[PDB]
Amino acid sequence: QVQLQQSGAELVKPGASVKLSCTATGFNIKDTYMHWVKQRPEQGLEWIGRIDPANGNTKYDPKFQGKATLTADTSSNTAYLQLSSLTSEDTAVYYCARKRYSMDYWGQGTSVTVSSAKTTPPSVYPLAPGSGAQTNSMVTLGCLVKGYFPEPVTVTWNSGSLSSGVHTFPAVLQSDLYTLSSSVTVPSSTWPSETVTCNVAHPASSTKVDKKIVPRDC
Amino acid sequence: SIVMTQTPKFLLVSAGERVTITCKASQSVSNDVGWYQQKPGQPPKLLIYNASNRKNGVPDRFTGSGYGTDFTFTISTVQAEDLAVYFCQQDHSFPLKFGAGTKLELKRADAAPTVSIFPPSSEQLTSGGASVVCFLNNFYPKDINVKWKIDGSERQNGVLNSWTDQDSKDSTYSMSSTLTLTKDEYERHNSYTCEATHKTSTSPIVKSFNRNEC
Image (cartoon, helix red, strand yellow):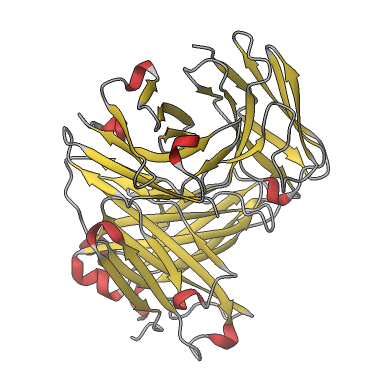
């Protein structure tokens, strides 16, 4: 019955401000300490600070004094982390946690990206096998998601129907644009006889693209 | 400013062995030490309450012990679902500090990759760019090399490689290699080759296609 609901992802220009919401359920916020944790990509966890919702007492790690301001509203049982003076070093996922009697529960986390680069929708390219490709029991199909910013994008195959043989690869940043690929391996008796479609979503640009894997036509 | 130093950063272990993660508090912390597990893409999950007290619904193979400066997290028998990054935490002094983390990696027998090569899509050719994609799937160990050859000539520019995290189902890795060129350069040449050199075989695993065919 205890869950922490965090706000959606944010892309902000450098020097801007952001406010994140952590809505709680199953426990009143004033009987516990709410904590916020920062995790830079491919890095560790950094304790930002702790808020006492009953009285408003705030203790921050000395590195987060001005950047992070923690405010709580007991009426909505919602804890807030405000991040200002944002730079690229603030690009991270921010979690909210509840701590009381050495007990902990964490939210899903909110991704904040700080960059001057503009939002760029991806280009989704179906990757069918070569025209003279080898025929076997299984056939591998691909999907290329190129030239998008910011992260993340979500890739699904046949709206979740195909999931066993999917390898979605981490994105690579180049010239302020991300590119990733996804592969799905299906039995050759099921393609092209059955449909295989690449479903790509890029929430930051409100982009949802479906690209069916059609055999190459010469 | 009680700093927690966590070792090792990377723990290469075999299934059925025992992993011990050590976190050293710079000053005395005593009871207020917690151990967290973070599966990829997931929030960290608490596993040890007060340096020896498992929370609940936690496999009894996850143990913790220590007092003062020395603290230890031990996994009795490493399993596939234990693939994650583990963090120690100190809540004794309010400047709360986490450990740097320990990335657990499962050891398994060498597996050869399944190499697939894909020509640039028809739609992308209208865009003015051409990306040749090579998939290397289900291989171990993680370290592997990909060589791109165009009409027999090795190409080292415009290549982006991306490794997947270890798959808990089979403890393997997958990698994607993308060669990006201009449309004019792609249409200039015909033979494009992806070569995979791995610890499994001294000879490279080769996949190729010809552009003058479709």
